[PDB]
Image (cartoon, rainbow, N blue to C red):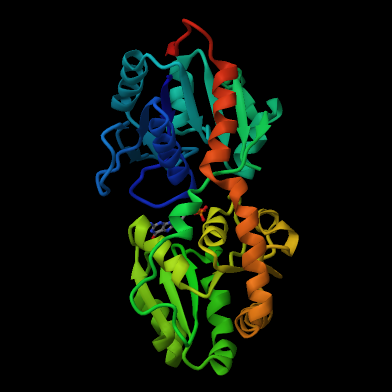
Length: 360
Ligand SMILES: Nc1nc2c(ncn2[C@@H]2O[C@H](COP(=O)(O)OP(=O)(O)O)[C@@H](O)[C@H]2O)c(=O)[nH]1
């Protein structure tokens, strides 16, 4: 039984891959009998387990010449030190130690058995001394290093949570349903590509629904869709259980991203749910879908290609069933059962009898 301290650099107020990774990992560890405490920025808009501690709020920097938009004040520095001093941790696991970040503040404040996970291409570069710049002395305090895609370990999901989620009332729809999940106002999420494919999709599937999960300006999007707006259904930013149900209820999950640096955990969620994936040919997505074995890859920012792919998947039951089968086999390697074991081996490696994380 270990005492583990974890640091998330991002508020839980907004959904994100790093945020969900840290909370779920904490839950998995506690279920195995370990003690976990999570430090993260102020998250007053969501309900959180009692083991989450607020590191305070990053406030805007009020002057020109900064190298960041937001900064944690002196209260945060004090909170971080107190949290470490009182935590008596066997391991400190920090996520995304970008500078400046709450994770880097924790790294500066602490020493002892420290592990870091690098979630993106940008933070993976920090495994190299040349990219650590004048923060080298702090990066040198990291004892174990995990790259999501040092040791490589993929981010985890609870497969059963998706596989066995209840269907939403009224689903599956005879008219078919394409699911989009994300903050659709952000251009990088590629809602614009799916909207440009919509006329061809509706011509072939006259009763099709685009089911949309995530926060954004629904009225602007409807206006963009013009006289096809009636094919759009918005759930808003729903809880995790509803999201899982939505995934299972859709006939296809569409991931039309124009770019990004993440692992692509939403594709894994769809695979777990038993829902066929059509995705942009991004490196991260190609890996999850085993180079097209476990889902359909479409060239990036290609609306005609995206329509063909979505129409193709909905029209060919054999093909769709094949992707789902290969995906359901594949996705077990991302389950927390398997993934958390790999992470614990790193914890074991960096820790040792009578050694604790302490304040620097
Ligand atoms: N419950 C819920 N989860 C969401 C919502 N939007 C995103 N997520 C989850 O947040 C994570 C997003 O991962 P990712 O695609 O990498 O988002 P990113 O971090 O912004 O790149 C996944 O677990 C999503 O299922 C939402 O509206 N509701």
